[PDB]
Length: 284
Ligand SMILES: O=C(Nc1ccc(F)cc1)C1(C(=O)Nc2ccc(Oc3ccnc4c3Oc3ccccc3N4)c(F)c2)CC1
Image (cartoon, rainbow, N blue to C red; front, top):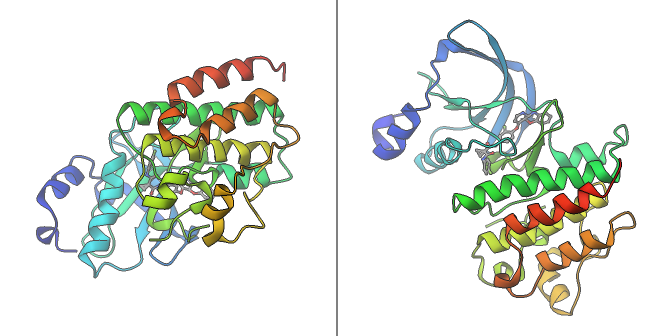
């Protein structure tokens, strides 16, 4: 890539988080995923002391479009100041002489939250699942305090580390590793379906859908609804049904997250408080 063609403010931000190429070993034989625009590999990052850090290494497939390259780097820069236990962090960006720049993330042992709760070999309790939702709410409370609007909050975009800590994330250009200007319409607030604008209050709607994903252990929402009909479906006066093991107060929280008026949906601060209380009523 020719750095001189990129936005100078973007390049300066990248240099503040740069990883030297010799400190990063990309295991091209160990692929985490491949999509149309990017791919992700296992990697080993060496710090100044020689300690090996297991990481995921995200790459573009092509480097010929300045728009794709700029967007790919911007995704990494957007993350750079996220410092919270429930938000995925950025290890850095490796600029190489040849090939794609590399976005380097701490490796998440248990992958994405949706596949984790769908895996019949794991047995999270109701309390565990509510705990996962509480952790997401805490990450979103942090992001909302930075005035950051996520725009694609969903279980598929949350990661789980080796301690089962949930990290809010966004696969971004690697999201295709559903969407139908490809939009996750079944997670979108009614006003966003109509205007395609997003706010923290539309993230709250998406969070309510994520809670429903948790309480169903990863069922697809609105499975019998055509993607282009979801607005009509909702406007008939409908919401996702209460899952069988979802406690009544948590379903009430979901219904508040789906309030027809964005301004009346609870803040993520309120959601953390309310879900903390519900969580605490469970022994296990
Ligand atoms: O997250 C982002 N931005 C952002 C936005 C909002 C926010 F609040 C926080 C963050 C970005 C990004 O690229 N995110 C991203 C996420 C997850 C990835 O995949 C990983 C990452 C680590 N280890 C796992 C690997 O996937 C797996 C799959 C299966 C089994 C195991 C793993 N392991 C990835 F490569 C990249 C866009 C910059």
